[PDB]
Amino acid sequence: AELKYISGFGNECSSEDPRCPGSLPEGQNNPQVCPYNLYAEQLSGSAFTCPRSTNKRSWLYRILPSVSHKPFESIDEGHVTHNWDEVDPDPNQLRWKPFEIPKASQKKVDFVSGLHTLCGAGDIKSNNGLAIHIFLCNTSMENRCFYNSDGDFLIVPQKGNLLIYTEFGKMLVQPNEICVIQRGMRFSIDVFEETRGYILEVYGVHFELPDLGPIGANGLANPRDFLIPIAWYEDRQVPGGYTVINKYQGKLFAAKQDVSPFNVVAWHGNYTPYKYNLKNFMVINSVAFDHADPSIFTVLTAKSVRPGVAIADFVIFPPRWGVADKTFRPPYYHRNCMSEFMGLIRGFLPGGGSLHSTMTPHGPDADCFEKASKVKLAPERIADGTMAFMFESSLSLAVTKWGLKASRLKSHFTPNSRN
Amino acid sequence: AELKYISGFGNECSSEDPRCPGSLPEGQNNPQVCPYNLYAEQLSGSAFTCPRSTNKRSWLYRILPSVSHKPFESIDEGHVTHNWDEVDPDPNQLRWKPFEIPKASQKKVDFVSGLHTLCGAGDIKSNNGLAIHIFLCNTSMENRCFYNSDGDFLIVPQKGNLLIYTEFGKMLVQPNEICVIQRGMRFSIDVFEETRGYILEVYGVHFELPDLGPIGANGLANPRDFLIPIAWYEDRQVPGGYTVINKYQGKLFAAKQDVSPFNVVAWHGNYTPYKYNLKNFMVINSVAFDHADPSIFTVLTAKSVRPGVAIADFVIFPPRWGVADKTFRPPYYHRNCMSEFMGLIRGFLPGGGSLHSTMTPHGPDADCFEKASKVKLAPERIADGTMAFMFESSLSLAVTKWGLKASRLKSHFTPNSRN
Amino acid sequence: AELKYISGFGNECSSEDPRCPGSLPEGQNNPQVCPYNLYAEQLSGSAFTCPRSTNKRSWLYRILPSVSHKPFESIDEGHVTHNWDEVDPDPNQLRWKPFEIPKASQKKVDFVSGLHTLCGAGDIKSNNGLAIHIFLCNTSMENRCFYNSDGDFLIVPQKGNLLIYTEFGKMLVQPNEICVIQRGMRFSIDVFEETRGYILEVYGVHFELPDLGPIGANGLANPRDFLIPIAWYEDRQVPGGYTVINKYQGKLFAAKQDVSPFNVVAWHGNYTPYKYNLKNFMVINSVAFDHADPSIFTVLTAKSVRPGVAIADFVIFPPRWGVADKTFRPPYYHRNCMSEFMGLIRGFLPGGGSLHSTMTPHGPDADCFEKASKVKLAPERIADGTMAFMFESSLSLAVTKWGLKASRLKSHFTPNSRN
Amino acid sequence: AELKYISGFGNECSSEDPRCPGSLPEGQNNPQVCPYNLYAEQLSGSAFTCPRSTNKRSWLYRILPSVSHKPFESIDEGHVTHNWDEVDPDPNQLRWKPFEIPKASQKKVDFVSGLHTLCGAGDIKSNNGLAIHIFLCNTSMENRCFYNSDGDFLIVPQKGNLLIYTEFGKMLVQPNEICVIQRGMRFSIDVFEETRGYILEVYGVHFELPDLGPIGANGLANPRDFLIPIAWYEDRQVPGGYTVINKYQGKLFAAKQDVSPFNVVAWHGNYTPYKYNLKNFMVINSVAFDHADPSIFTVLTAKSVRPGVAIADFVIFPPRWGVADKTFRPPYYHRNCMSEFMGLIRGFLPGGGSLHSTMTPHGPDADCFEKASKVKLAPERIADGTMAFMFESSLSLAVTKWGLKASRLKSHFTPNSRN
């Protein structure tokens, strides 16, 4: 059965499992007894006193409240790490071949077990910074879920579909789609093959859409294209206990409870998981001359504690027309304030990546420069059949121990002749 | 001799007439005696206490200060008017054929004499609103200048070049170029033929560049393309008196002085006249699908007293590629908050225009809809050889008495077939 | 008996008449029965939902509430007017000799009867703009008070002391002092001789202190120097009725009540009348070279609906040292965005004034230029024995009918010689 | 030959080496082939999506792009350090005699080799904080340059001129002048003698001018006095390789390339190096009574991540008149939120300094108090022949290991007598 979705980034939504119509309380949040004898539970994603445009919360009407669980116990963190101080700084570009996925025949690995932190920056203990992770797995999560007490996850499938269970409902997320699971939300992932993808985590902040500026009221990632799960529950007791895994200050902990956490019959609010299909990105760019800054391809952004400065942006390079005349069309030679992780959904193959450091020069290789300097220019299709992306940060992304171990022009100047 | 210019919108500039090197005071603004025995005079374009990014002023080092003039006397306002309450509201679209230019053989008319207010809105007496004027002239201004005590002028030549004298230097402004003369600045215009063009006046505010949003750090009207006159003076006594014409609260006044006002030998500051060639506009638009909002073509904007809302924007429709696939390419059917004056530099011919009122429906005619709905889409050149523009306002532009006197689809729905 | 005062601009104050200690309710504003069987009455000077730094209100604990009065009746407006459209615009400077004060022997005139509006701008009916008034009186107000429903009054005595009764207590305001009475506050004034002074009224807004910028945390008008009346009441029945005069939309109305309105035994809050002695102004200016902008002498300012732009500022020119070396010390030649009323507490004599219009040139006369260009510069005392001031506006101040009726350099350039 | 400069802090500049007129592309940034067959390279100094007033970038038209270099290698960091946690906190004032400069006869030391970090605060790995360095050198940099990937440098020469090569052109910076080199910009310094000076580094932020507040539109450091290098190139191959030194996360790295990096023939933008002569500071202070806060001498400031709070300010104490009457003229007794490094360009001699810690009391010694309490006050010259300065921070500056090793009133109360 193909899943159904609600749409509208940032919306105040209302959703009831179709088996229990009117499971939302009418005209209030906190009835003495909820419809169907459910429990009301608020999940807050912002301080209580945020202005309305940034105040985030959802109410869940659930069979048992989340408090019904045993005490947390420390579990091994595997390759989830935030110690950016383990490894010495190095400004040289790093490159990765497509990360190796464990074979089910050798070792069964679910999404949580196959999480590997590649790089990051900032102090997680001060709720400030970001991390990039790679997931490498081959088996569905069984009777266990995950939630992040530290921040939000932007998940980017590369190889293999993800069937994601959340308290708000299910999402199927395919390569070329992305999804966001926000702080505190429990989720579990089914997979269907040897699975690989990328994750951008931001601490203490949520993703937003960029203001459009002169682009105006429509374009880039249209709000209607963001899809939110519809309410779905299971009332399922779990012999031996269901395990809730919690990432808290970068460490992992496990608590057992009697039932699946996905027992929310109805929910309302504006704090939810969501997904987005990158094919819907309404690409804006130059249509006369010159080369537009790659910020013009921004899909989502997350604020830093410095005003106007993002801690991270998610930028794509989508199939489009290229038409600039009298113009060097490839990316210009460049030195910038950001550090940049490049990935490829579909210098590296899909599933690998590269990391470029703050203020290190980059630009086209000699062959690219050559061709683009001499070609007869005409409208052309660019990037059909591909989807590269970048996670860029105002901090200096530093590789982890695991990331390091996994890693791999002439003068034409004619001083006497202007033209 | 072709004029030289300084460049950089908003710059703190420094300019000396090349005949008098070092006419700017070194390291100060207010010497006891200025270099060359000039007088220092500050022209403020903002309150003294504005934040730096919006604090506007220039210092002029001049042969005689501006105070040296006789008392103002009232002169006839001709067709300059601000009484928007003279004429009854009417939401119907208005159209104008190319405004008639007086023949020199019939009547000599200079730029000030040929100023005709077409429409406007707001209370000039509260420094709030805008007006659109048409200039229709055939003779250079002789021993007289103009300045506006009420606001700023964006001048758009249509037929004929303008040679503009300002206190800061000269500008030659051709059709396809625009210039801005800001509040209080004296100017005089030479013409070379029967001359016609458009003017957008905004009261109590200056034009700015739009923030670029995701477009980033380059694109649309690049700051380097805004050109500012270099210092130029004449020390010229005028038998019988030079006449300074002042528009003050919408009324015209004349004062005589002994010398030309263009006696500034050197100047510095960030409050100046400027010009811009529309051919340099770096056009941003859709390169995959859909139709971008026309705000994406904004050249200059002026703020209203309501936050985020412009009192006026200057928008162009420049030569470009059109490439959106699976898309209705022409302007979409539309109802909006703005009122819109359309002009054409090069439904009306160049030199005419149209006025569309707030929230009145508009969109393509039946023939346009037809062609664009059925065409096989491919990359095409749009608007080559043309330059239409719009002055759009958050207020409801109302025609003047003069403007009024000068003025002149089927259902395809198949309910049973989605595709 | 010399009056006592509380101090601290913007303070949340608490004041009880010393005859009735503990007349403020303890720990609340709205007791079922107030101490001493008083009534609680809130006077709000801002919308309820303003941020705390701008939320203004006071609670009054009074013998009878203000509602206890008969219906308002229209009375003649004398020379209080707001019709700026009565008189044609004129950019020429206006000057006034010291306004004539009526002799008591000819006609008894109290402060309200002797109010004459000189000039103003903006639409009072939209709560937007300002007016400048002159008061010319010779007798104390007897059994009547005044309050302004439209805005705030900054009162500047020139000749004669004012003994001002307010609901919050008494103030004695002498020439060289100023006071503010804010919207809605009832007041009555005693005088002691033929009395003259100036008033700046601002509609729909309050005065504030300017941010100090680099001047930092102390200087200009120190907050401690603003003095607020201490609570004082009279419980006084008035045979024949006490008259309350109300300026409402620029018109005057009169209502009778049984008792004096000054029956507030105790009060608390941050919305009060206040006074300030100009001798305490901590003057900031240049101490090396150049001539500082006269904004540096700002005492109070009131915001316009355009951000960063004041509707009015109150600026003084106080006794100080002048020490700039290699500098033209007098005011520089100048054209600016403001319109400017000049007054003199102690081109016109004390009690007269001048009005300079937007963007009209001004600057030193030939004699002043001469002396200041050639003098040997050394530290000197400036303005001892004097106190000129200015009310400056971002709108174009227009004279009233009454104001109109009351109203009255060479080239040195050496092109071949820089030095 | 004396160097020429462009002027205007924050300007959008355009500069071409005079040997190659028209080396800037006309009307665009990204031609297919640049004039003179140069390469276009953008240096971004801000995120792409900053508002215009803070969006910083420059385009460089250069013989070879910056990417043309070999891989970075780690080099020894000498006395450049950011480990503020090496040394235990200590609130006591520290003082330094003029730092010892190495003799050329003993050891040749260029500017990079002679960099010694004195103190600092914040986490460089989170792009947050500041450091103060002392440079002690005696030989010009030969075939090597430096750039900072972490932040901006404010350089303050004390002994010896600096001839600074940047990609944007040359600057000669003398004692009593300062210069700024911003993040990512490569530079090399020639010296002429045993050289010593101070450096303020701020991480992740740029310097700005302070808003002037009531001082208005002119005064303190006037924008026209900030001087920017004019374009200058060398096309110079370097046998054995030119070395580029990179400070990246506080560590030093070296990469070799074939040519000098100073091969930019033309450039435009608003992100540049600049210099300023402190003699031009237009000093503002008290001219009647009282002692102004030393913020009034602020030359440049850099924002912290807390609003309104600077991470650092650069404050000077320039030659001026002192004239306050009835006033204690010396600095007042004081405890404040800041930590303060004092230096002296021309308790310590020129070239030494002191560090005062957060909230530790300071104020005049007994002798100073005595003299200033009893003197007959009259206008006096202050600080002629001297230029002390301060780098003050909202963080608590902590000394380094090197800095530590280099380091060295009565009651008058008369209770019974007010006057």
Image: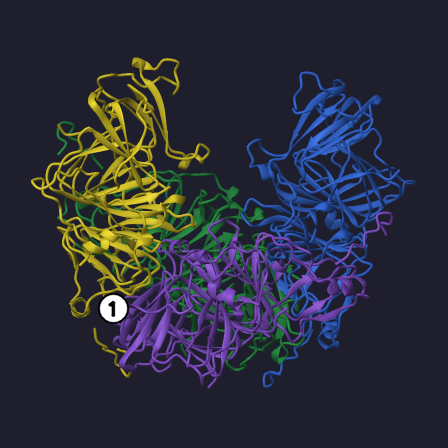
Chain colours: A blue, B purple, C yellow, D green
Horizontally, residue B17 falls left or right of residue C188, namely: right
- The image position of residue B383, as x and y in percent, is 67, 71
* Chain letter of the residue carrying label 1: B
- The image position of residue B22, as x and y in percent, is 33, 76
Which residue ends up furthest to the left in the rendered image? C105
- The image position of residue D125, as x and y in percent, is 58, 47
Q: Is residue D306 visible?
A: yes
Q: Is residue D268 above or below residue C236?
A: below
Q: Residues within 10 Å of mark 1 (few under 14, many from 20)?
A: few
Q: Foreground residue, D40 or B154?
A: B154
Q: What is the quadrant of residue B184 in the picture? A: bottom left
Q: What is the quadrant of residue A32 in the picture? A: top right
Task: Find numbered disc 1 in the image and state the secondary structure of the residue it sits on.
Answer: loop
Please give the residue where the numbered disc 1 appears in the rendered image: B71
Q: Is residue C74 above or below residue C240?
A: below
- The image position of residue D297, as x and y in percent, is 33, 53
Horizontally, residue C196 falls left or right of residue D363, namely: left
Q: Foreground residue, B127 or C253?
A: C253
Amino acid type for the residue under numbered disc 1: Pro
Q: Is residue C249 above or below residue D285?
A: above
Q: What is the quadrant of residue D6 in the picture? A: bottom left
Q: Is residue B185 visible?
A: no
Q: Foreground residue, C259 or A266?
A: C259
Q: Foreground residue, D249 or D17?
A: D17
Q: Please tell me how many numbered marks the rendered image carries.
A: 1
